[PDB]
Length: 162
Length: 129
Image (cartoon, rainbow over all chains, first blue to last red; front, top):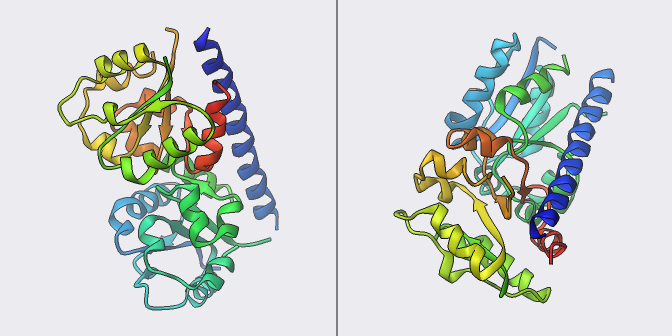
């Protein structure tokens, strides 16, 4: 009888997951509907070899043009000026939201300013409470998750913007 | 008997487990966790079997520290199965890196701390009484 409630929870979790995938796909459709390069990707020094390499390896196979060596954050400058120089070069921009990213200690106003738009944040190995601590607004809104989709699926989803 | 039991790595007990146990105790549920913290040399399947006997439901928290303990593949793929009384919780872990250990566990949907808050996960767990 105890398993039945686990089944009910299972069904609820499944419906919620369905709604979430629908939401992000609907926002990307509105984003595409609304530059020499396709994407640029802002990340920390620690995430570069770990996740970013795999993502650009995934996107370049689909035929996307990216450059990630340029946009490594040293945590010594403004986030705004780093995302605007990339919007001048690329069609879209990606920010990898991780523990290494939040450890740089960025001004609240800039994180509040990260949120049609051409910028797409990707949650990588973070909890909701943790993101809510640095900026509750950034955590409240929707973004891509590495906990929900594989790197390859994420790459296809991004490629739908071009 | 107890309501839940929550197995976990020794590293996540102060970061997430203490918070969840606190939240679930604030909701009137009785759970125990210090007895079900696992060492690198353990049998996952037998440990959960001890857990389903002194409590009604079981919780496994899937984190980098949990996977750093190299469990057998058969014991992660067995978390899934058959009637199921166990509830996995994803905490700060990537999809692809779960696949490295168990694809069957990665395709199964579970509670995700990147989606809900600890208080929200607590309520959502309390719905099972």
